[PDB]
Length: 102
Length: 109
Length: 194
Ligand SMILES: *[C@@H]1O[C@H](CO)[C@@H](O)[C@H](O)[C@H]1NC(C)=O
Image 1 (cartoon, protein in one colour):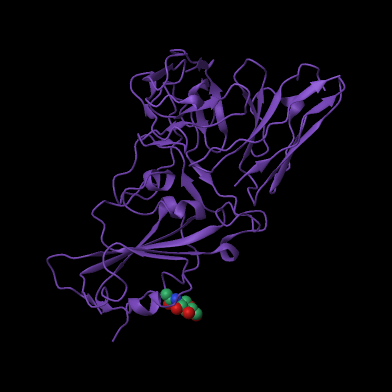
Image 2: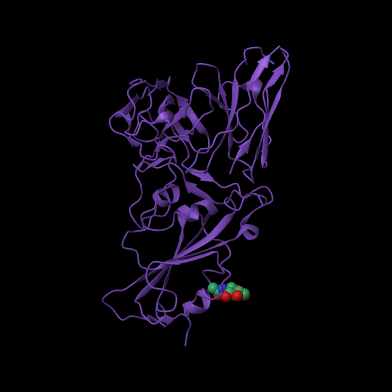
C-alpha cells in the first residue's frame, strides 16, 4: 500500500494544528506518529492512538483508512512523519508534512 | 542511546557501519537500520530479529546486517549513488513503533 | 465406512489463536480429501507432498490437523523455510515437511465491528521455535539486562499482542482461517487410507 499525507503548514504560535495522512486501503490501528527536528534523529509520538512519554500537548489520533493527529508551543518547528506499522517487507513512511510557525 | 560509525568513502567500495547499545542489550530486540537521503524522507534498509532472522528492502537488497556482543554491524559492497545518506539505529516494537534511535551517521560516495 | 472427521476441523466454530493452535489427530478411518479439495471455496490449497488426486490413494498412519487464524499478508509465511512472526514465534514448520496447507478468508465470521481482540500472537520471544513446537508461556518478556518480575512496563512487555480485525480492513489485514494437514507414515498399521 501507499500512504499520502498533507502538505506543509504555516501556522501561528500558540495554535492547535492538525495533520492527516490517508492510507491506500485499510490499516485501522497500524500507524505511528514521529517527530523529526532538523539535524536530529526523529522522535516518535503516537501508537495507534496512545502516546509514549513526552508529547502530551501534541497527542491525537483518528485512524480508519485515513488517520490524523492534532498538536501550539512554538518549539514545533520540525517535521511530522507517519509510519505504517505492520507491513513487514516494507516499512513505508509517509510524505511527511513539515510545519513552520508565523 | 547508540553510536555512529565510518563516513564517506569511494564508489562501490566496501561500506560498513556499526552501532552500540546504551542500556538495552542487542540480543532481544528488533534492531534496525533506517536511511534518510539528504533532501528526502525516511526509508528502511534492514531489520534484525531476536531469533536471528534478518530482512532487507528492495533497494540495497545486497546489504548484510549482523548481530553479536553489543556491537551491531551493517555492511554493503555496491555503494552506489543512493548510498550517500544518513543512517539511524532503532529498536522496534512492531505494535509500538521505532523506539529510541542513535545519533545517526552520514556516508557519501 | 466411517469417514474421517473433517467437518469438525474446517467447519469448527472457534479456531484458537496462532500461538495456541488446535492440534487434532486423525486415524482409524478413511477420508475423502478430494471432495474437500474440489470444493474450490478455499483461497489457497498448497501441497508439499503430492497433488490432491494422488494423495488419496496413499494410505497413512496418522494425519495431524493444525487449525488457527492469522492475517492475510502473513499466510505466505506458512511453509518450510519462511521467516517472520508466525514462522518463528508462533507456528514453525520443518524443512522435511510432508502434508499440506489449506487456507481461506474468514473476514465476516472472525471480524468484529470494532475489530475482535480475541486472537493473539507471541510478538516477543528470545529464540525462534523449533519445528512443530508449541509455546503458550505468558510470562512477561525479558527485554534487555534488567528484569521487572511480573510488572508490565518498559523493557519488559507482555509478549502476546492482538489483531485489529475491523470489518473494513484491507484484504491483507482481514483474518484468514488456516489448517495444516500434516500426514505421517510410521512402523504401524496404516489406518488412514483413501
Ligand atoms: C462445512 O459445511 C458446508 C455446508 O454445510 C460444506 O459445504 C462443507 O463441505 C463442510 N466442510 C467440511 C470440512 O465438512
